[PDB]
Image (spheres, grey):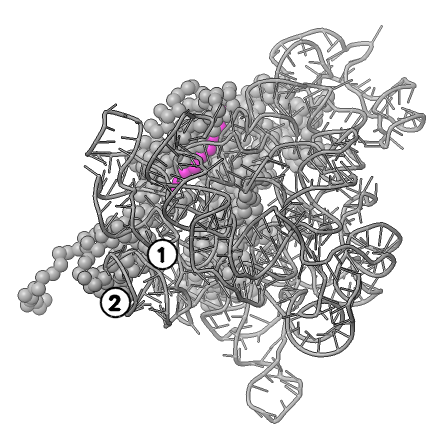
Amino acid sequence: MLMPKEDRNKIHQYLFQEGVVVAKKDFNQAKHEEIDTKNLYVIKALQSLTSKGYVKTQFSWQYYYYTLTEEGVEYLREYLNLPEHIVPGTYIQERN
Amino acid sequence: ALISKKRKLVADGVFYAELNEFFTRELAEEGYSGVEVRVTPTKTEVIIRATRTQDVLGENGRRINELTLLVQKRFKYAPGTIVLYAERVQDRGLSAVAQAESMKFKLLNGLAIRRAAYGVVRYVMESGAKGCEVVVSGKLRAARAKAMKFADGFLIHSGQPVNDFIDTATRHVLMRQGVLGIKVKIMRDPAKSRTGPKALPDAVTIIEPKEEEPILAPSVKDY
Amino acid sequence: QQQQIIKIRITLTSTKVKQLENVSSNIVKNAEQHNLVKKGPVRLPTKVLKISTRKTPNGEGSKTWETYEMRIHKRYIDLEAPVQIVKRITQITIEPGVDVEVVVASN
Amino acid sequence: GRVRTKTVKRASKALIERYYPKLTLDFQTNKRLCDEIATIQSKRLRNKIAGYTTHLMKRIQKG
RNA sequence: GACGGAAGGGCACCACCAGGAGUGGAGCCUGCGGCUUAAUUUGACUCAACACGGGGAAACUCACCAGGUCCAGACACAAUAAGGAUUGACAGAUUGAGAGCUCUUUCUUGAUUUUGUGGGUGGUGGUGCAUGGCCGUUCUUAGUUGGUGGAGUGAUUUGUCUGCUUAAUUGCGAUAACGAACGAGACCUUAACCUACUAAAUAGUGGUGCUAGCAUUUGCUGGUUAUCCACUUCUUAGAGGGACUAUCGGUUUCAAGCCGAUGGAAGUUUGAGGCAAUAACAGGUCUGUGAUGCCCUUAGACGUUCUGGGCCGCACGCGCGCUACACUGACGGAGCCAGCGAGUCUAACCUUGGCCGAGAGGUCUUGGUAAUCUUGUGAAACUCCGUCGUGCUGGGGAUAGAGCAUUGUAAUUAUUGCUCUUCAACGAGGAAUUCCUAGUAAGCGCAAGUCAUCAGCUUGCGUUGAUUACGUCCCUGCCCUUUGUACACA
């Protein structure tokens, strides 16, 4: 949906801090905790990078496990413009 | 809050059948073989004691840091508890998923409907499988009847404590021509399991005495 | 205040009664190691948590009725316990899903 | 209407081949001497086989 | 092999013969038709569809009839936005929704892709004669089978049997068979016996700290939101015993039987439950799976918004039931019984009471996330004592009418109750036709399930409890031997 991307990049802000992009199920509720934007139209750009990979997928229990893949560097050199190895392919917790 | 005595063991499955639906469905390529649930307070023991536990290090933060915060962040457990751990599963005859996932990469090629089936299961047919039951159905040949009722084993069932020795599985794959449903039944041994009842009541062995005494012109014994 | 014996209502519960009687036994046996004065093991009634539905996924045929149920086993005890015997309990008397917390009173 | 069952009928002749010269008419001490050392799996699977041992050697003295 | 209006065997309260409950009579919910409405969405139509699909449906549901906005068009690959793409819009003309639905129309609006050939596949859309998984039925049943040997060129057969018993292909006994692997049986539960235990008020005990009083016929009714708490048997089970058709007479191929009698908590696989094998139904579920091959559609949608009829519309048909035809009954007083539970979490569920008003019920309070409180579920059905009489009635409450409350943003086509107006049918019910043999047939009533509210329903829980057959092939149903078969989607 035609909607400005500081909405999306507060939520991609919520991705690279711990590693989650997860939507819930309702319409006109718009209150998911710790992803505090709308429940439904955030999906509208969340598949928009799925069509060329970039993220994994399952539905079950309508849980929306849509979390980024190994190629979460080259598009977020330009969509968040971050220096990698902070939440890229070697985001070490400590050792576990 | 203020948890009743009827709100966590009937609600065992809100977390325990959460993981068991997760790694049946998300990345069950690992050959899932249960979690060793000892839930300590403010820590979370993930033990995927599976076939591919070399993926507990991995990149040390590529996919594990997802799995720190996917099951733990959908019912929204508060972070600061989650620990991950693994170890290789073994003895691959006594587990349903061990030969099921030994068929979950053979259902594209065009192997036989029987050749892989009774060959791998003779890891335990000679070491503790008496009566098994494998049906690999779906539609392998477009007709009216689509079912292969494969029967193999040296059948001993049933005395009704059945859960002492049974494995169960059912799988699916979305191929060109519809689903292919692979449900098996693998039969563990109570004689190989070394636990509790040695065998359900068939195997009863009888020892032999000394040779019984004669009239015995007897004795002078004073120790 | 540490190490007084002031009549505490230690409460235990579990699922299968083999390991619930296990946990109570090696704590009342650990009520021997310094001899807690006590009118102790309250062999409390155990529970039945029945559901009774139709497990069929279609409404046809001679219809079906089953049950499926958890066994809440449950041992309230009348301890009289000190401050030492509550500490090491999170990984002693071990079984899958040990659950305990005690209010420090009975009167 | 409650005649006996086969897997305890055949089990005694691999069992009372051991200790024939016992198991007399009074059916109490022999009953636990039927339950003597064996690898049994319940109590009334063996009290039936002791009552099997009770009735089927009491009648040898019927000829 | 399957059949037969062929014998023979057996056995069947999903058929009888005694029975004990009866049905379909009325009215009225509750389904399935049809009726047709513009709409009565949809599957299931043979015991084996039809108080089934959780289905007691206001919205939520909802797949039909009605309307109108999001496109909720990921995008493989690319025309049109930069002196402007997408369009919300005040106030108004429409318009349930200021639904800028639509317009009257110029404020907002920027790289956030409107989309452009084509493609996500949303689908409660067809396809269980595309399906898996699952669930029923064949069958409340004894039926399967290899290892070897025997007969037959071979399909096959024998073992699994003319007898007798059984709940039984269970056992005995006969024997080209022997020895077995199954299912069943066995196994296991439970309302249980255990004052013997590891063991006692979030739980139950003789006592009695403080001891009011009837009464002195000297210990009783007792209480004491704990006083020392007296104590484990009742409450509850950690493993175990105790019962294993247990014992003698009758009759028995002396077995396999099973009874007269009875120690006993248990003599009927204890009564009843529980998972129940080989082989398959074009059984059924694609209107529960976001698992679905194909095809209709892919935003002018069969997704998805938000209010109405609906599945709740009417000669009539058939399916499950509920109140009854009263006078071992009805009304009024006295006494008074269960177990099952499920109960609030950062919200408002169960709730004795206080006080109010006749109820419906309402405000502060009583305890409880739970052997704490509900609730001692004193309820009905029940026991005892006064009032009603041959009538459609002190049985009955269909039918419509008015008023008061409760739940829900929201009650009209009425969510339910309450108080009065309306006060009927119907009198034991046709050729049609079921269930069930001891705390069970029967009587009645409370939890839970759907549950804001809506049980005339369905599981259980219970409180009180007879019968007569004591079993069998004519009707109906099923397995086995023998024959016959021009049949094999039999």
Determine which quarter of the picture holds residue E442. bottom right
Disc 2 on helix, strand or loop?
loop
The residue under label 2 is which amino acid type? Asp
Q: Which residues are magenta?
A: B164-174
Answer with left or right where residue E398 lies relative to residue E211.
Answer: right
The residue under label 1 is which amino acid type? Arg
Mark 2 sits on what residue? D26
Specify whether disc 1 shares its chain with disc 2. Answer: yes
Q: Against E317, is B99 above or below?
A: above
Tell me residue E259's x, y (percent). Answer: 37, 65
Residue D2, labelled with which disc?
A: 1
Residue at 28%, 66% (x, y): give it: D28
Tell me residue B170's x, y (percent). Answer: 46, 33
User: B129 or E439, which is in the foreground?
Assistant: E439
Residue at 19%, 55% (x, y): give it: D18
User: B62 or E413, which is in the foreground?
Assistant: E413
Answer with left or right where residue E269 lies relative to residue A67.
Answer: left
Q: How busy is the neighbourhood of tag 1: few (under 14 within 10 Å), some, or many (20 plus)?
A: few
- Residue A96: say if magenta: no
Which mark sits nearer the N-terminus, 1 or 2? 1
Q: Chain of mark 1?
A: D
User: B146 or B218, which is in the foreground?
Assistant: B146
Q: Against E12, is E337 above or below?
A: below
Q: Chain of mark 2?
A: D
